[PDB]
Length: 245
Ligand SMILES: [Fe+3]
Ligand code: NI
Image 1 (cartoon, rainbow, N blue to C red):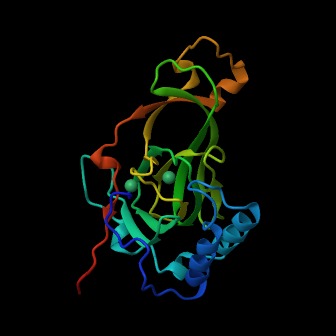
Image 2: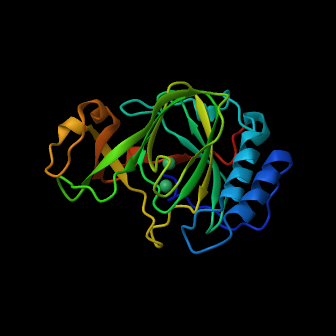
Image 3: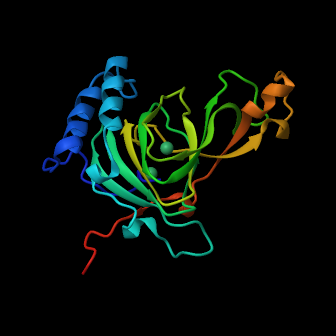
């Protein structure tokens, strides 16, 4: 939903100070080692989480008065603006700017570890993980366990998702203007087989499949997720390079 944007990957010239400089230096260490998709060491995860947990929106130069947090479009949900900070083959750092009612629709992060901090605003998050080795009603629909279903109002601390835990499938819906700082390791890559897949979600009771038995009081904790094709409305838009007078 941003991996189509053209950016200078591995850019040589950067200008960061303070917390952003520390964040960048920490990411270079945290994500450097092992084959693609390697989850960083637990010590390095804790280090990066703590660096991110010191960061306030002012430290990364965003505030809710910026134009990125307002949309006038009608017929669809508000445009979400992508602010590129840095990317290379091992990780990306970026900020998503959601006007009220902006959405990043339900999607996965295959082989990816993602650190996320809500910088300001009230955001609803729904997230899931697959139930491994479970029956399916159809090839494109799979059983998932609900992990998060809550509003978050900043100030908030950093969360983490893993390739197969911590809510690898999630949907973000802004209730007020929101800014989210994400560190994504590694980024999506269609050439590398890390596609961004989107889903429609359904209550457990919407599909009755043989070989699946869930107790009554646990059913609300599960969902069926159906793969669906990316739509133009899913995609974030670029920020203006030059914003004028
Ligand atoms: Fe995501
Ligand atoms: Ni993308």
